[PDB]
Image (tube, rainbow, N blue to C red):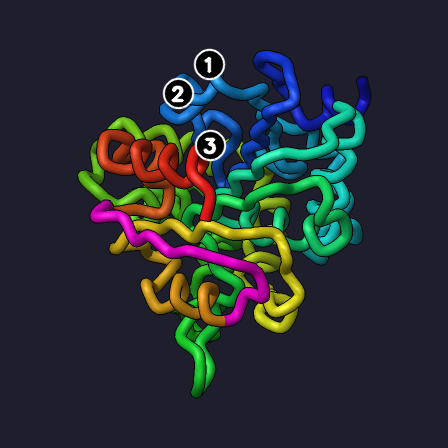
Amino acid sequence: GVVEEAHNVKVIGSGEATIVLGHGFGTDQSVWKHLVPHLVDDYRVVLYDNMGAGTTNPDYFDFDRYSNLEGYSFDLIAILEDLKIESCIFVGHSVSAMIGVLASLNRPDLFSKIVMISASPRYVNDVDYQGGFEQEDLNQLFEAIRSNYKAWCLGFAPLAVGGDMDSIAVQEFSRTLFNMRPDIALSVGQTIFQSDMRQILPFVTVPCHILQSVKDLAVPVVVSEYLHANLGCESVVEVIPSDGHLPQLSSPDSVIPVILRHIRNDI
């Protein structure tokens, strides 16, 4: 199918119990490689890539469509409808947590639970909210992307992944970052880092499990609490004693058991 080719959709197993996993900026569905082995016995598992990932065709990246996170949420519902999925657990890494939230506002019936890893509704600080970034440092970030994309990827990957700067996960993320087309990377980085989901959190109704590393470049721990306090749905937080924004890839021994408990157990 067109949709499923374009998003590199992969479906493993069958049956009603279904889990759909959405990745964050700069990576692709391979971020889930240490989680999926533990899901396939119990669930139909659905993997897909966001439009604009380096594994996707840049001719399909419609700048107007993806200038709002809504564009991605429409892609997610389309995939679910294409696959005839009437209900799933959705696991959203980084921006995909907010993409799943938006999709659940339009179609809450499609989701029984959202499990967020490394989520944030707002990165920019204001006098009454800490998201982790001042606008001036975002401006410098974007200028670096603009001036030398390879150099930016090499410097950003170790910061994002955390841990040892020479690790396999840092190398993997370095590689997936650099596989994006530089103009798409710049555009999507701006859209995500300038986003603001805070105002819609009270309207969420699907239960949410809010998971993050205690040390995350892009997600201060107070953001987990902000999500918990302001989401309209039932929610639970668990901060993991791990480092990094992609901790399911880089620290699976400590992280995967936590994710599995939240998938397998309801609030």
Which residue bears the numbered disc 3?
176
Residue at image coords 52%, 71%: 230
Which residue bears the numbered disc 2?
38
**Does residue 164 lie above or below 225 as drawn?**
above
Residue at image coords 61%, 52%: 206
Asked if marks 2 and 1 touch (Cβ < 8 Å), the reply is yes
Which residue bears the numbered disc 1?
41
Q: Which amino acid type is marked by label 3?
A: Thr
Mark 2 nearby-residue class (10 Å; few <14, some 14–19, many ≥20)? few
- In the rendered view of the protein, which quadrant contains the N terminus? top right
**Does residue 205 lie above or below 159 as drawn?**
below
Asked if marks 3 and 2 touch (Cβ < 8 Å), the reply is no
Relative side of 239 to 74, left or right: left
Mark 3 or mark 2: whose residue is earlier in sequence:
2
Nearer to us: label 3 or label 1: 1
Nearer to us: label 3 or label 2: 2
Relative side of 49 to 6, left or right: left
